[PDB]
């Protein structure tokens, strides 16, 4: 029987540049809370990179490619920081960084809510052939109240904490296990919430 | 259903320490908590357990620690976390696990015909006092949830539901240590006062 993609024994993941803590696991589908994934400074820098990229990509600017408004503008431009972090993430996720879509940065304001959703795409969808297989959500700041990552079919919540992350995979043969990774963010009620996400495809993506 | 544990938001502010709410299994309620004990406090609890043993030997003039300033401070902090007075607690119980030792999964509440059934336990806090190289997870087999040991972290869970099938979902055990050793402190809380 094919084992989980995430393949780590023990209570830490030793990456080239950082020791990540394995905090807790829901065992099937695999959902893993991870500590110390990003430094505080790295969290702050990813937020700043997202803001500065946006401030200079408006209408009339030279590089306002149309697709960035619908809706790829949340992916960071490549630089030495994003390469460093994607390399670390690849050790955590056991999949080369070439399979990653790249660091996607998003913020949630008070009382905003998304529906719970799946991260993988629908069958016969455009991305079905080389679908997403696993996700890493990195919390880039502390949230005074609300903002939990909630898995409603499992009744499991992961609360945001700067530098912490939640990993989950949905590449199971039994499709019901993949559907149990349905998830959304509980509303922020005090503060704001910043996350970086790495979505990993079955095959190479970039 | 309103749980005994009653905390909104992402931190628990006690009188002497801010605790992080890391993750929650919502029913029955299992909460992973960060920053419950300082590293020094973890080291001290272990030392205290060892010093208490070095005095119980034959000819001298059990896992529960004696009451002193350290245990009083910790039980006060724990009482804010668990929303139950420290007087309901059995007191801090220190245990260690060596490589390849295992206990059967079990409930923390007592059987109905137990001497403790009339004042039964209602909730547990397990505090990890050291780091464990490999193994040692706290596992809930009916829920398929594991909490890995991390020095200064804790797992809280309660089993005081009227829906008794929820209490029966809190079956738990420690998975064997395969590298290193595991030290924990546990506070078990009774429905009424105990001490």
Image (cartoon, coloured by chain):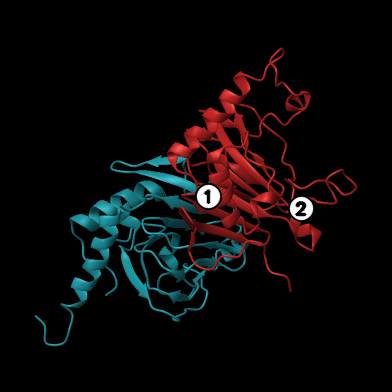
Chain colours: A red, B cyan
Residue A54 placement: quadrant: top right
Q: CA distance from mark 2 to mark 1?
A: 21 Å
The image's mark for residue B23 is 1
- The image position of residue A173, as x and y in percent, is 79, 64
Residue B94 placement: quadrant: bottom left
Callout 2–callout 1 Cβ contact below 8 Å: no
B128 w.r.t. B9: above or below: below
Q: Is residue A94 left or right of residue A64?
A: left
User: Which residue has dot 2 on it?
Assistant: A179
- The image position of residue A193, as x and y in percent, is 55, 32
Question: How would you rate the neighbour count of disc 2 (Cα within 10 Å): few for under 14, some for 14-19, many for 20 or more?
Answer: some
Q: Is residue A205 left or right of residue A21?
A: right
Viewer-side residue, A121 vs A92: A92
Q: Which chain letter goes with mark 1?
A: B
Element under disc 1:
strand
Q: Residue at point 60% right, 19% down?
A: A55
B148 w.r.t. B5: above or below: below
Element under disc 2:
helix
The image's mark for residue A21 is none
In the image as oriented, which residue stretches furthest toward the top?
A: A60
In the image as oriented, which residue stretches furthest toward the right?
A: A124
- The image position of residue A137, as x and y in percent, is 60, 44
Residue B1 seen: no
Q: Is residue A10 left or right of residue A58?
A: left
Q: Which chain letter goes with mark 2?
A: A
In the image as oriented, which residue stretches furthest toward the bottom?
A: B59
Q: Residue at point 38% right, 73% down?
A: B181
B55 w.r.t. B133: above or below: below
């Amino acid at each position: 029987k094919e084992q989980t993609i995430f393949d780590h024994k023990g209570n830490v993941i030793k990456t080239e540049d950082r020791e990540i803590q394995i905090i807790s696991k829901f065992e099937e589908p695999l959902i893993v809370v991870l500590g110390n994934v990003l430094s505080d400074e790295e969290c702050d820098e990813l937020i700043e990179l997202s803001k500065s990229k946006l401030a200079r990509s408006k209408v009339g600017s030279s590089r306002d490619v149309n697709d960035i408004r619908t809706s790829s503008g949340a992916f960071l431009d490549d630089n030495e920081l994003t390469a460093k972090i994607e390399k670390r993430i690849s050790s955590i996720m056991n999949v080369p960084a070439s399979h990653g879509e790249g660091l996607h940065i998003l913020n949630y304001e008070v009382d905003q809510q998304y529906k719970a959703h799946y991260d993988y795409f629908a069958e016969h969808s455009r991305s079905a052939a080389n679908n997403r297989i696993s996700t890493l959500v990195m919390y880039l700041n502390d949230v005074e109240e609300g903002g939990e990552t909630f898995f409603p079919k499992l009744n499991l919540s992961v609360h945001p904490r700067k530098g912490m992350a939640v990993y989950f995979e949905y590449f199971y043969q039994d499709q019901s296990l993949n559907e149990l990774t349905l998830h959304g963010g509980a509303p922020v009620t005090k503060g704001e919430k910043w996350i970086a996400t790495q979505w990993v495809r079955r095959g190479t993506y970039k």
